[PDB]
Image (spheres, grey):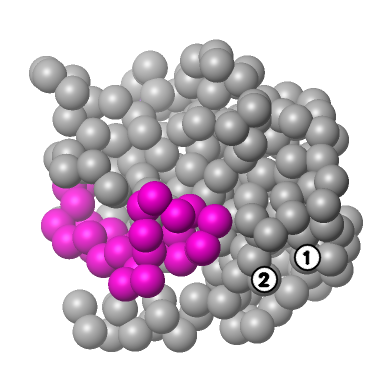
């Protein structure tokens, strides 16, 4: 997250860190949202590589013991069957991860609530992106979980020629684009939390930013629209 602030450690208890095994250690690669005690929602592109993955719930500082973490292996990966890794603009950037164990819930570890199917946010709706991704274009990962306030940019504006044009689909949510605040590499797969009827819900799964940089004016961060995939999610969980 470029232009973020440090999150309070109990603000976003559904955020997870998706990590892969790297030598004798683990490296953060993406975010995710805990959606059942044994299921995480993330981006398909985060799991393209043939790596050993784990999830960390209750994580705040990637580089320090928080006293709240639970570490769990990924047992099964179910990528959306229409996903194509060389065509992120087509959409379908979503995957579900079945965890090897069911995590225990507490103020640091909670299920993300998802929007009702079909819900589309009005332009300029209030949302926060969260993650440990780069804090500058071509920078480095955050140590502590960051949040940034990123208002939605509706489809009509986001798919206009000076924004994303054809590359953004109605199956996506755009947010931000102010040139200061954005998602960045390492935020992919995590939540976009939007405040609706008094309750935050996870409306987006972080998918992509501009090849020209993270915080680029009129290139809002682009998310998979969770509300387009409610039946898919429920079908995967029911059949696994
Ligand atoms: Na930690």
User: From what the image shows, is residue 166 above or below residue 186?
Assistant: below
Residue name at image x 64 percent, y 66 percent? 169
Residue name at image x 59 percent, y 75 percent? 227
**Quarter of the image where one finds residue 223:** bottom right
Residue 214 numbered mark, or none: none
Do we see residue 8 in this rendering?
Answer: no
Dots 2 and 1: beta carbons under 8 Å? yes
User: From what the image shows, is residue 82 above or below residue 143?
Assistant: below
All told, the count of numbered labels is 2
- Sequence order check, earlier mark of 2 and 1: 1
Which residue occupies the extreme left position in the image?
Answer: 24
Q: Which residue is mark 1?
A: 155
Residue name at image x 19 percent, y 52 percent? 74
Screen quadrant of the N terminus? top right
Describe the element under mark 1 as helix, strand or loop. Answer: helix
Q: Is mark 1 within 8 Å of ligand 1?
A: no
Magenta stretch in the rendered image:
72-99
Residue name at image x 60 percent, y 70 percent? 171
Q: Which residue is mark 2?
A: 170
Image check: 204 left or right of 157? left
User: From what the image shows, is residue 229 above or below residue 124?
Assistant: below
- Whole-percent x and y of residue 226? 56, 68
**Nearer to the camera, 127 or 217:** 217
Reply yes or no: does residue 85 show up in magenta: yes
- Whole-percent x and y of residue 179? 81, 29
Do we see residue 74 in this rendering?
Answer: yes
Image check: 179 left or right of 80? right
- Whole-percent x and y of residue 161? 82, 52
């Amino acid at each position: 997250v470029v232009g973020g602030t440090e999150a309070q450690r109990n603000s976003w208890p559904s955020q997870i860190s998706l990590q892969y095994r790297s030598g004798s250690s683990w490296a953060h690669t993406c975010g995710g949202t805990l959606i059942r005690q044994n299921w995480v929602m993330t981006a398909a592109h985060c799991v393209d590589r043939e790596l050993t993955f784990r999830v960390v719930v209750g994580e705040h500082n990637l580089n320090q013991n928080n006293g709240t973490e639970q570490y769990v292996g990924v047992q099964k990966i179910v990528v959306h069957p229409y996903w194509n890794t060389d065509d992120v603009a087509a959409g379908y950037d979503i995957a579900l991860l079945r965890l090897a164990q069911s995590v225990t819930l507490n103020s640091y570890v909670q299920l993300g609530v998802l929007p009702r199917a079909g819900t589309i946010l009005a332009n300029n709706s209030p949302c926060y992106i969260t993650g440990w991704g780069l804090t500058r274009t071509n920078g480095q990962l955050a140590q502590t979980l960051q949040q940034a306030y990123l208002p939605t940019v509706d489809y009509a504006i986001c798919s206009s020629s000076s924004y994303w044009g054809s590359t953004v689909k109605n199956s996506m949510v755009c947010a931000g684009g102010d040139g200061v605040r954005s998602g960045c590499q390492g935020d992919s797969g995590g939540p976009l939390h939007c405040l609706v009827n008094g309750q935050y819900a996870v409306h987006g799964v972080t998918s992509f930013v501009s090849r020209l940089g993270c915080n680029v004016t009129r290139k809002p961060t682009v998310f998979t629209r969770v509300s387009a995939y409610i039946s898919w999610i429920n079908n995967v969980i029911a059949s696994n």
